[PDB]
Length: 99
Length: 99
Ligand SMILES: CC[C@H](C)CN(C[C@@H](O)[C@H](Cc1ccccc1)NC(=O)O[C@H]1CO[C@H]2OCC[C@H]21)S(=O)(=O)c1ccc2ncsc2c1
Image 1: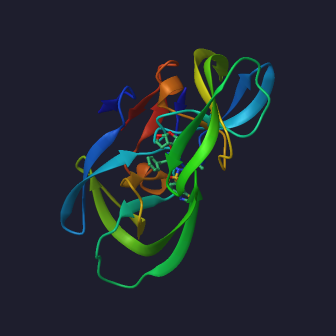
Image 2 (image 1 turned 135 degrees about the vertical axis):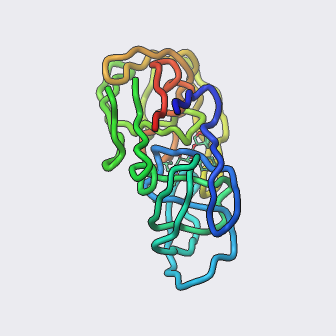
């Protein structure tokens, strides 16, 4: 599909067996999800943006389904105010910017 | 153009007569640029990101050219980690997400 940017580009995703709303975010290197209790091993990480840094948990090889398009990669979990789909998964679903 | 996302979507912009590099950021409502001198009046404002809120200078109706496309709108100037072009100007140049 084609998503205009009049409004936040929020879409439904499926991760860890849950449905959630997330931003398709070309400004995010990595994918960052709101606090959730995923199983498996993780590594601590810190990621920075406007206002400073937050501490997140890095999970690897996590399956996410974005508007029916499957993707698998690194997902960061932490106290973000919004679920963010970053470029590491946007490339996997064939997402491009066009103007 | 069609921009893929295996690399950061960095582009050259012209603002206040000066060339700068900026990130096309579909996850940003607003356009926030690093500290710089801009002509015209401004008002203090606050904006929040992943790490908290910062103080910015708000310049309204600023001319800004993004890869040869003209936009005129609000530009926030402050301690952002990177120059970001948000949806308020991405819409003006006709940018959409496609997958
Ligand atoms: C340094 C480049 C930008 C700031 C990076 N950000 C993604 C950006 O889309 C962010 C994503 C975001 C969106 C909403 C709340 C918090 C973060 N939006 C944002 O900060 O926008 C601000 C400016 O417009 C306003 O509207 C939204 C907030 C304001 S981010 O969320 O901090 C982010 C995401 C993944 C990531 N991986 C490594 S670093 C890193 C940083």
